[PDB]
Amino acid sequence: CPLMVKVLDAVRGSPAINVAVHVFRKAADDTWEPFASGKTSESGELHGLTTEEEFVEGIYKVEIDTKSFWKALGISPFHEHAEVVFTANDSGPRRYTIAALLSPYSYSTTAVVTN
Amino acid sequence: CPLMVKVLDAVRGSPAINVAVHVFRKAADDTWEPFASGKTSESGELHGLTTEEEFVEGIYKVEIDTKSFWKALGISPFHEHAEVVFTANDSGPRRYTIAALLSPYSYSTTAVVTN
Amino acid sequence: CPLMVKVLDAVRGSPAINVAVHVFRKAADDTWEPFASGKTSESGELHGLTTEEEFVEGIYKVEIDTKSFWKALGISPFHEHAEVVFTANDSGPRRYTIAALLSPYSYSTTAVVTN
Amino acid sequence: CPLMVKVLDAVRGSPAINVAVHVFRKAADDTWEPFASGKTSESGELHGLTTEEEFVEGIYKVEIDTKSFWKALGISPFHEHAEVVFTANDSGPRRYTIAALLSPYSYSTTAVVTN
Image (cartoon, rainbow over all chains, first blue to last red; front, side, top):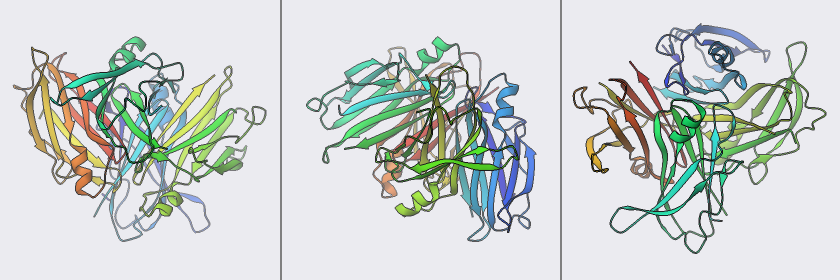
């Protein structure tokens, strides 16, 4: 599990469940290619996006579909999604946790990277 | 104006208005003594808490009454208040902006220290 | 001045100065088209990106070049840039402040929308 | 495990290890009484602070000793500590995770509360 995404709700103080997550990888022609996708669990976590073999060095974009999450709770939020763009495995394989903390008009995102 | 407090509302994406703010200075006995207080303005700021002459080196505590703020809105909050504790140091000329971004179950606070 | 961007440095507790900022508007083809850009000022703000007349309803992307900012400081950053994607809506009178608070492996972004 | 504290480092993108944590409970005479204390592990987590039996309803203060953490890394941070003040178990027993994300001049804290 070299990539995990975790999403929390700062309004209710709870994991954000069923949040859609899309991962893309920058291609040789400078375009964002689809890499993996999924939805968070009851714990607000999304495991199994990828394997160490497939998760090669590159520039990755993690898009968390925060608007649909808020809408479904009856809230009209400011952002369309939260996006996280980063270079991965450029020094060798690492394990990445991408965490997002969501409010209707604000979010924070943090990476925890372990060897 | 060496000390300013600014509060934002992450749920509505607005300044947090009429929020009570209390500042304490730590006394020789280790107890907190009242130092300055007020309510934030329509822009979510609180100016004029102290002067250069009164704001001497020491340990200060800024308490932001977040709980009454959320209660007025109708949103169950987690925290009793937000607390920012720091030592004022002389270093050269310095202005302190204590900012706070509020969500019902999360807050962040940042110090912006400039000349 | 319907759109302003403000960037703070969480590691030094200062405005983030000379940070490049690019704004894109989403075209009919779904591609991002350049819309406005600049660098933050000594106060960490970027004013004058657009006018009321040009800032019509649509989907916008604000990209903040955080990676070059940390590189200039000497601190290894995680992210390639910070990205804020949102729909501008008409609704009554409105001013948009996109704020970003930067750390090497974390950032937060908040929209302050006022009249 | 009705109370857990987790601390992350936003400069390195890593758990904050060996961070001292002190918990107090408000006493009938309005004073902060010592309740429990400990230090975060290699995972940045602190388990075993208390038991469901001892963790009665009340107002609790969780003090995270962020200054000593930064100093030991050679950084002179702004805050003395991060403090989290909240009412607990006022609707029945809950499980509380208090998370703190640390930068030298900024921090955020979030509570995740589960039944």
